[PDB]
Image (cartoon, grey):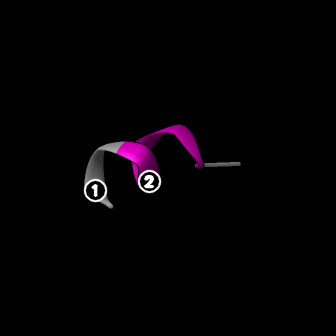
Amino acid sequence: GNHWAVGHLM
């Protein structure tokens, strides 16, 4: 799932 990208967002 897209969880890594979330780190850059919030």
Residue ID for mark 2: 6
Which quadrant: the C terminus?
bottom left
> Could you tell me which secondary element the residue under label 1 belongs to?
helix
Residue 3 coordinates in the image, percent (x, y)? 59, 48
Task: Give amino acid for label 2.
Answer: Val
The answer to if 4 sits in the magenta stretch is yes
Give the side of residue 7 with respect to residue 9, left or right. Answer: right
Crowd class of label 1 (few under 14; some 14 to 19; many from 20; radius 10 Å): few
Question: Amino acid under label 1?
Answer: Leu
Q: Residue, x 44% and y 53% (percent of image)?
A: 6
Cα–Cα span, label 1 and label 2: 5 Å
Main secondary structure type of the part rendered in magenta: helix
Tell whether 3 sits left or right of 8.
right
Q: Residue furthest left?
A: 9
| Front in this rendered view, residue 10 or 5 | 10
Within 10 angstroms of label 2, few (less than 14), some, or many (20 or more) residues? few
Tag 2's secondary structure? helix
Residue 7 vertical position relative to residue 10 in the rendered view, above or below: above
Q: Position of residue 9 (x, y in %)?
A: 28, 56
Which residue position holds label 1?
Answer: 9
Q: Which residues are magenta?
A: 3-7
| Tag 1 near tag 2, CB within 8 Å | yes
Q: Position of residue 7 (x, y in %)?
A: 42, 46
Residue occupying the far top of the picture: 4
Residue drawn at x 30%, y 44% is: 8
Q: Residue at x 52, y 38 (%)?
A: 4
Point out the residue furthest to the right here. 1
